[PDB]
């Protein structure tokens, strides 16, 4: 027959991750 | 000797990415 | 011809997702 063929190419990079968490709460407002 | 076999199937896709970085802080609350 | 080559390696992990949305506003100040 012959030697085994070359390995296939690496798979595709995985899907992008999900959107990150929402940022932290802003500081409370100044007294009037 | 014989010729090498056909190239193999491409690999499976990678796993999912991590969630993104946290968002920026909210704005300051309105003044009183 | 030889036998088929092996399946390739699994792909790498995906890139991190997009940066998150801004946080909510602070509370209104008091009178």
Image (cartoon, rainbow, N blue to C red):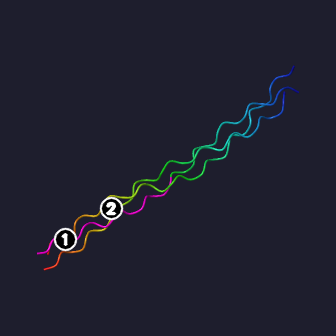
Residue lying at 77% horizontally and 34% vertically, measured from the top left: C5
The number of callouts visible is 2
Labelled disc at residue C22: 2
Quadrant in which the N terminus of chain A is drawn: top right
Instruction: Give how far apart the Cα atoms at labels 1 and 2 are.
Output: 17 Å
Is label 1 on the same chain as label 2?
no
Question: For this rendering, which residue is in front, A10 or B21?
Answer: B21
User: Which residue is the extreme one toward the bottom?
Assistant: C31
Labelled disc at residue A29: 1
Residue A32 in picture, x, y percent from top left: 11, 75
User: Which chain is home to disc 2?
Assistant: C
Front position among marks 1 and 2: 1
* Residue A27 is covered by the magenta coloring: yes
Residue lying at 15% horizontally and 71% vertically, measured from the top left: A30
Residue B22 in picture, x, y percent from top left: 39, 58
Q: Is residue A13 above or below residue A1?
A: below
SS at circle 1? loop
Labelled disc at residue C13: none
SS at circle 2? loop
């Amino acid at each position: 027959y012959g030697p085994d063929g070359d390995p296939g190419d690496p798979g595709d990079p995985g899907p992008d991750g999900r959107p990150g968490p929402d940022g932290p709460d802003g500081p409370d407002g100044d007294p009037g | 000797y014989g010729p090498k076999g056909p190239k193999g199937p491409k690999g499976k896709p990678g796993p999912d990415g991590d969630p993104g970085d946290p968002g920026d802080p909210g704005p300051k609350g309105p003044k009183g | 011809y030889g036998k088929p080559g092996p399946e390739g390696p699994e792909g790498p992990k995906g890139k991190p997702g997009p940066k998150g949305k801004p946080g909510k506003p602070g509370k209104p100040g008091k009178p």
